[PDB]
Length: 226
Image 1 (cartoon, rainbow, N blue to C red):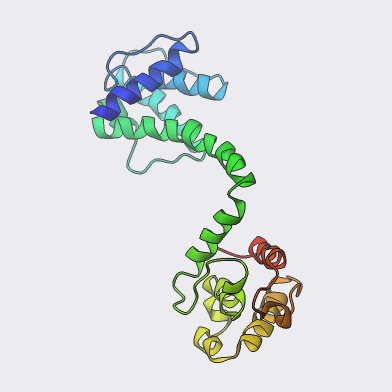
Image 2 (image 1 turned 45 degrees about the vertical axis):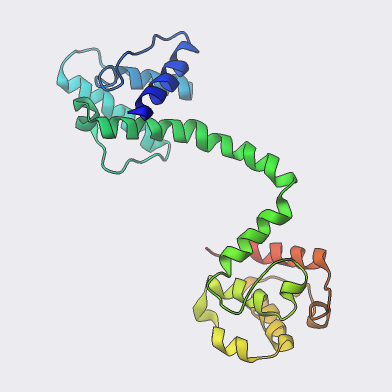
């Protein structure tokens, strides 16, 4: 309804901005597949075959190429197929457009957004990762990259979460902070190739070195499974 007006505008914007004519009704002019074929051509800088006949067959044919392409671009659609679009299914016609917008714009833009974010909110964005990763683990609460890692619990939680068959979590909560670390470091080492950068005596202290933690933490993460 609203998504109509705006999606129509957006597509029409895409069109005008490249010498191509606009459409009137988005649940019509879109059916025969032609327009969507244009949209994708301009969007991809590619040449796409267009069937000229004005009969259902061709409509389905064109719309199939459209979907075909999206698929080629790793943009698969849930319950959508030629006929849907060819027939004017409101719900799904939009759902398709949005898929395009989402892939070529919205998602595209995110790479840049991260670059802008990656220089400033680095340390902060990595903390919300660890918090989310070790959420399930009750006895683990990470607020920073210093004290929250002293009891050595947080270090294991990170490992465990993505390979619980590696060791017993309850078995850990039992051992001392020193064991808890000697362990994690040893585990990560044997099963992840990650070198034992830190030493327990170094991490189990009032204020442990922030840079050293983050550097080991990032080491772990690189080779971590998800």
